[PDB]
Image (spheres, rainbow, N blue to C red):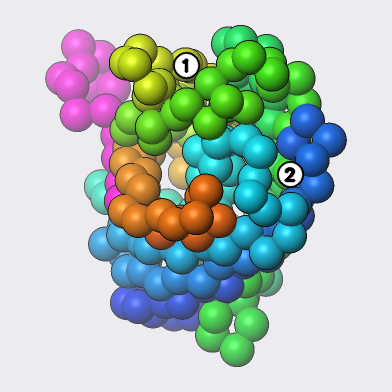
Amino acid sequence: SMVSELIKENMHMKLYMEGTVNNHHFKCTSEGEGKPYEGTQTMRIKAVEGGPLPFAFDILATSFSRTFINHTQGIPDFFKQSFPEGFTWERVTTYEDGGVLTATQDTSLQDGCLIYNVKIRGVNFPSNGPVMQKKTLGWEASTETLYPADGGLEGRADMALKLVGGGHLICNLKTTYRSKKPAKNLKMPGVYYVDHRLERIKEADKETYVEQHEVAVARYCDLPSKLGH
């Protein structure tokens, strides 16, 4: 495992988020910490404008952290290598009942603290669906597939949202990750997988306060190969 000198064993983060969902404007802020090489992180999140949010907070949860993924098996770490400049990500999440949420994020490092700035736009969430009715109960774990494209990385995942009464609502995540460091200074990974488990620990007051935890690991497929891979 390669160590990037700026990314320490313990790191703190601060986040600002603004956006609109179904034309409802909001802002959130958060602060947290984690162990970047162990793959673990916690965020404590406040809705500071537009609360109580009229939509399930669950649809924002993936928009609050690539530095905190445990890279195993010598996979080059596109994210940790990107400091001090940092990196960006742009995502479109498509829900099977029509809701679409886009998010664009900047990650920087300022005085040793990771800083996140996120913009969100959600449209077409059905008024009768479980997001706008706030009838969701968190995410299942997921596996994201990552692969190089044109100097950056592309990521793909299907995520399963638990519903009140049982059942799931599925969404598809398409993400473009881009380093702010020049290509010559990055060792690029090939195809690899990130296993994620994002769990809500605490909440208060119609989700205006949320504490979330995630563990995440970058790995190859551990199945045998008939081709030597």
Label 2 neighbour load within 10 Å: few <14, some 14-19, many 20+: many
Residue 142 appears in the figure: no
Q: Element type at marker 1?
A: strand
Q: Nearer the viewer, residue 1 or 209?
A: 209
Residue, disc 2: 120
> Toward which corner of the image does residue 219 lie, by quadrant?
top left
Extreme residue toward the right, this view: 23
Residue 222 is a magenta residue: yes
Q: Which mark is residue 200?
A: none
Residue 61 lies, with reference to residue 36, above or below; the image says above
Label 1 neighbour load within 10 Å: few <14, some 14-19, many 20+: some
Q: Residue 85: percent from the left, percent from the top?
A: 67, 71
Q: Earlier in the sequence, mark 2 or mark 1?
A: 2
Q: Amino acid at mark 1?
A: Leu
**The N terminus, quarter of image:** bottom left
Q: Is residue 94 left or right of residue 199?
A: right
What residue is rendered at 63% in x and 14% in y? Answer: 128
Q: Residue 127: percent from the left, percent from the top?
A: 69, 18
> Toward which corner of the image does residue 139 lie, by quadrant?
top left
Residue 99 lies, with reference to residue 14, above or below; the image says above
What residue is rendered at 25% in x and 47% in y? Answer: 73
Q: Which mark is residue 169?
A: 1
Residue 229 lies, with reference to residue 199, above or below; the image says above
Q: Which residues are magenta?
A: 212-229
Q: Element type at marker 2?
A: strand
